Image (cartoon, rainbow, N blue to C red):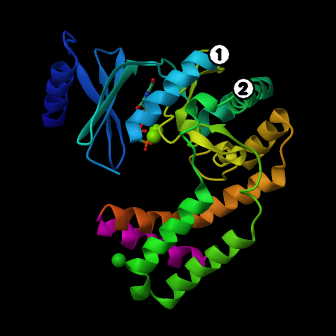
Amino acid sequence: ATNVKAMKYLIEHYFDNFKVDSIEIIGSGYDSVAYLVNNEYIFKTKFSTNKGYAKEKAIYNFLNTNLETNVKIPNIEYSYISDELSILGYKEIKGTFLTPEIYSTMSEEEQNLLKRDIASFLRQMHGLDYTDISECTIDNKQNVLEEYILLRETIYNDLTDIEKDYIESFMERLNATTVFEGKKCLCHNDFSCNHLLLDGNNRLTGIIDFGDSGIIDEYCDFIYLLEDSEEEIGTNFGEDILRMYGNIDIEKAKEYQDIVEEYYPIETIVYGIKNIKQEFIENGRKEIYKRTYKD
Ligand SMILES: Nc1nc2c(ncn2[C@@H]2O[C@H](COP(=O)(O)OP(=O)(O)CP(=O)(O)O)[C@@H](O)[C@H]2O)c(=O)[nH]1
Ligand SMILES: [Cl-]
Ligand SMILES: [Mg+2]
Ligand SMILES: [Mg+2]
């Protein structure tokens, strides 16, 4: 139980008179680990990476001050932020994560109420005056262009023709699309069903992981709601939510999701380059072949 011991130590060291009586791992990413401490607190942690926890903390603070909602989000009680180590702690939001299986046991009315809850939460968050967090802007198109330049400066010339063509074909679509020219607002920006918590009546009770959140295209928060995969509910779910949300071009939302999805293998390669992780470069290149050959 080595990781747990270390992180217990660090929590007690940086947070005076916080006492860890229990601690377990409840989640992880490639760069992070989350712990449930005293069956009450979530502690999210990471070591040296590529101002992440600073922003996420600022966003929680901004949202807890400004949202009027019964939906719970993390409320940061402990933080330690440095280049080499960042920790955020908050009381665990209780509930059951939404999944496709759970959704399929819900009555039609239950499903509608959950969809309305989501639409309402997104309408309220996207309608906030974000002046107070105006530094948290994210420009996805410009980010992609910069990543493309990094590719050109590093490994692009060693890729295969098939890989190059996939990339260039994406860049050509990026240049022709209009889906980055619409409304910008504060978005969750990783808005998948594994971040949505339900209460005992299958209503939306909490939303977690605003770690990628920022001021960005309004379309961003529909990308997973529109996704047809084993992990998400399905395209009709996102469509209905978009109709409830109102005043948004559904076809552009879908175009934006389709473009993000096409980018994925390239995003994966770029992550590998930036983090010096060859396995990610390989995985993304292989995925380009998988997509190219899908019939
Ligand atoms: N019940 C519950 N689970 C939570 C809460 N906060 C985090 N979790 C659990 O911890 C996991 C990791 O938290 P999360 O913020 O998503 O992770 P992360 O550090 O951003 C890494 P990634 O972005 O890949 O999710 C979640 O998937 C979930 O299982 C919370 O308040 N309530
Ligand atoms: Cl490789
Ligand atoms: Mg997460
Ligand atoms: Mg996250």
Q: Quadrant of the N terminus?
A: top left
Residue type of the residue flagged with mark 2: Gln
Q: Residue at x 45, y 64 (%)?
A: 268
| Distance from Cα at disc 2 to Cα at disc 1 | 22 Å
Q: Tell me which numbered mark, 2 or 1, is placed earlier along the sequence.
A: 2
Q: Which residue is mark 1?
A: 201
Q: Quadrant location of residue 86?
A: top left
Q: Quadrant of ligand 4?
A: top left
From the Cβ of disc 2, is ligand 1 less than 8 Å away?
Answer: no
Q: Which residue is mark 2?
A: 124
In depth, the one of 85 and 106 nearer the eye is 85
Q: Residue at x 65, y 15 (%)?
A: 201
Q: Which residues are magenta?
A: 276-295
Point out residue 274 in the picture as x, y percentages from the top left corner. Answer: 35, 63
Q: Residue at x 77, y 51 (%)?
A: 182
Disc 1 residue crowd, few under 14, some 14–19, many 20+, Cα 10 Å: few
Point out residue 3 in the picture as x, y percentages from the top left corner. Answer: 17, 36
Q: Secondary structure at mark 2?
A: helix
Above or below, 152 against 199 in this view is below
